[PDB]
């Protein structure tokens, strides 16, 4: 779903984010 596609995108973004947290 559209609204869902947004969420799935959060993971891709958070990817490089949580990377710095490491």
Image (cartoon, rainbow, N blue to C red):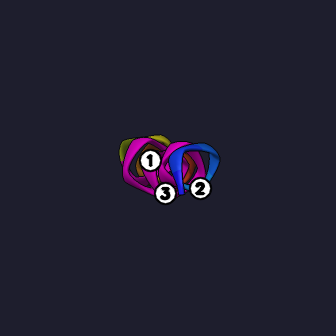
Residue range corresponding to the magenta coloring: 5-15
Task: Determine the residue positioned at 49% across, 58% down.
Answer: 8
Q: Nearer the viewer, residue 6 or 12?
A: 6
Q: Which residue is mark 2?
A: 4
Q: Identify the element where label 2 is drawn.
A: helix
Q: Nearer the viewer, residue 6 or 14?
A: 6
Q: Earlier in the sequence, mark 3 or mark 2?
A: 2
Q: Which residue is mark 3?
A: 11
22 w.r.t. 3: above or below? below
Name the residue tied to disc 1: 9
- Between disc 2 and disc 1, the foreground one is 2
Tell me how far mark 1 sits from mark 3, CA to CA.
5 Å
What percent of the width, then of the height, locates residue 15? 40, 53
Q: Earlier in the sequence, mark 2 or mark 1?
A: 2
> Does the residue at mark 1 contact the one at mark 3 (Cβ under 8 Å)?
yes
Q: Which image quarter: residue 1?
A: bottom right
Q: Nearer the viewer, mark 1 or mark 3?
A: 1
- The secondary structure type at the circle numbered 3 is helix
Give the dominant element type of the magenta stretch: helix, strand or loop. Answer: helix
Q: CA distance from mark 3 to mark 2?
A: 12 Å
Q: Residues within 10 Å of mark 2 (few under 14, many from 20)?
A: few
Q: Give the image location of residue 5, x and y in percent.
A: 48, 51
């Amino acid at each position: 779903g559209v609204v869902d596609i947004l969420k799935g995108a959060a993971k891709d973004i958070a990817g490089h984010l949580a990377s710095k947290v490491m």
